[PDB]
Length: 165
Image (cartoon, rainbow, N blue to C red):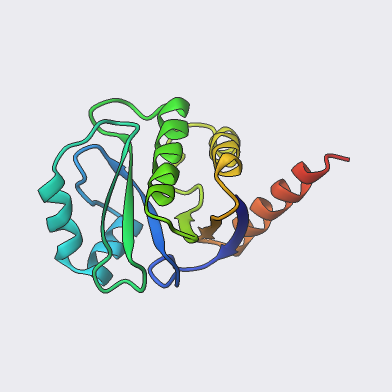
């Protein structure tokens, strides 16, 4: 899948859907998740409540409320079970296969940030990077970064992979 990295506010992303690292109970908590809930409305949480629990490693899709996208794909990394590298690799794949099922073309992840949580960020990058690279080219994947500095490092890491020098 085509990949781009930018600093930004993922509640402003203007595409098909966004991915939200979550717990398997689909309870939207602190931070970015909090932002998605405020800017979208409680309909996102209601839809989440409707689906109820899922299995750590999987992903559930709901509407996006007033967010300028169509779907929020929710990627259960922790909760029931602890968040491990495989937890994240599986959750990322899931969320992607979800975009595929739905015929999407543009879908943004909030990059690193709350995918890492006490794991090595270098490592989480890899797993998400490989997973994203396996996705079809019909899909173009944006990683919204909180700080520009982290956006740039995502870019070189991408660029340093295309070669390695």
